[PDB]
Image (cartoon, rainbow, N blue to C red):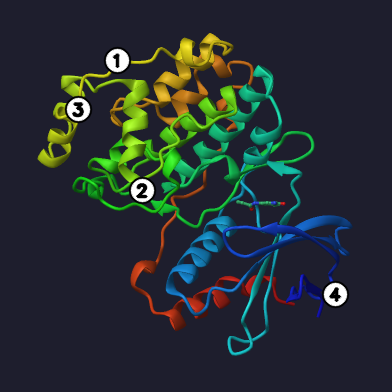
Amino acid sequence: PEMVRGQVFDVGPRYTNLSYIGEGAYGMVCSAYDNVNKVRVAIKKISPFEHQTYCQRTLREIKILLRFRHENIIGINDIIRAPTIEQMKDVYIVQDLMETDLYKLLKTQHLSNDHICYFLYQILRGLKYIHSANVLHRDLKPSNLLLNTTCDLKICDFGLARVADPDHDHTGFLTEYVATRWYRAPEIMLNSKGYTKSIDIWSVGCILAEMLSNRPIFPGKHYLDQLNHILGILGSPSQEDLNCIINLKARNYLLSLPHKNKVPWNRLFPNADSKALDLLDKMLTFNPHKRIEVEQALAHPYLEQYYDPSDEPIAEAPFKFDMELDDLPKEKLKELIFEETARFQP
Ligand SMILES: *CCC(=O)Nc1cnc2onc(C)c2c1
């Protein structure tokens, strides 16, 4: 079995000529030549079977990605693992090789308005499909958006995804949250579990702002600082938007703050297209009930060059986790991953 930086990276004879790319959320990632399709591919190594949380997220990613089929969502091409549960230690997930991600691109490259518009269209096109399946991505951010050499964009990492559950979205003030801090909607810190589609639109709004300036719009350094970044640009919420927050600890926190005025978008982004800033405003709305939905966002004048609902497909059915993955033991989740990956065995 081949090794990479002194570690087993055991992808059978189908995949050869490994080149270390780097580490990701799950573990080691290499490119390799796929001797069947005659193209280089990306392979990530996962070792999740001791920890219930890595198990849960790995199973979530696999079940979703195998069920989804969309041009702006990364697919799984192949999964490599041992033939029996007893011998299964690692799982290798094979995907299309992509030149870069939007995180790396934003660190190194100025984007033309045309590139911003095209990227945003593709993000929303993919998001339309995910939401149509009643799924929330819940961790949209530049590093989860992959690009190829021709700027085709694919959303990746469904490890934190959930089935939407708006009726159970309410929580108390300062409730801990898992998803990446700088892309968290204000309501996460106030009264939301992130179980509604509006959570993902906020993240997309944050990504659009980051494309406009190459800098994160709300780089909070800790849980509550994230809310204070957001309010520093949006300004103080209105009476009406405050009244929608029934929880007294959250309400009274907001009432305790000094009055902050809105920073106009055209002063933060003096080079931006005015239609881009109109759409940005609508995605970065404080009140999640007033926030634009994915289909409205696609229909916004900024995206007129691309908008075509007949070419923005939806999922054939809503997605469902058959068992509640949250309280399954470690051995049961390994068996589930074994079963979910069976279709790739010879
Ligand atoms: C979702 C994050 C991710 O998969 N990152 C990534 C990095 N480098 C890559 O090269 N090919 C692919 C498919 C990727 C993904």
Marks 1, 2: nearer the viewer: 1
User: Which residue does the image show at 33% across and 15% down from the upper left?
Assistant: 262
Front residue of 55/225: it is 225
Q: Which mark is residue 13?
A: 4
- What residue sits right under mark 2 in the picture? 164
Marks 4, 3: nearer the viewer: 3
- Quadrant of residue 225 within the rendered picture: top left
Say few, some or many: other residues with alpha carbon within 10 Å of mark 3 (under 14 / 14 to 19 / 20 or more): few
Q: Is mark 1 within 8 Å of ligand 1?
A: no
Q: Amino acid at mark 2?
A: Ala
- Sequence-wise, the earlier of marks 4 and 3 is 4
Across and down, in percent, residue 62 comes to: 56, 63
Query: Separation of disc 1 and disc 4 at Cα?
Result: 62 Å
Q: Is residue 32 left or right of residue 301?
A: right
Query: Separation of disc 3 and disc 2 at Cα?
Result: 32 Å
- Sequence-wise, the earlier of marks 1 and 4 is 4
- Looking at the rendered structure, the secondary structure element under dot 3 is loop
Say few, some or many: other residues with alpha carbon within 10 Å of mark 4 (under 14 / 14 to 19 / 20 or more): few
- Looking at the rendered structure, the secondary structure element under dot 4 is loop
Q: Are marks 1 and 3 in contact (CB under 8 Å)?
A: no
Quadrant location, the C terminus? bottom right
- Looking at the rendered structure, the secondary structure element under dot 2 is loop
Q: Amino acid at mark 3?
A: Leu
- Sequence-wise, the earlier of marks 1 and 2 is 2
Query: Separation of disc 1 and disc 2 at Cα?
Result: 33 Å
Across and down, in percent, residue 275 comes to: 52, 12
Q: Which mark is residue 44?
A: none
Q: Are marks 4 and 2 in contact (CB under 8 Å)?
A: no
Q: Amino acid at mark 1?
A: Asn
Across and down, in percent, residue 253 comes to: 17, 35
- Sequence-wise, the earlier of marks 4 and 2 is 4
- Looking at the rendered structure, the secondary structure element under dot 1 is loop
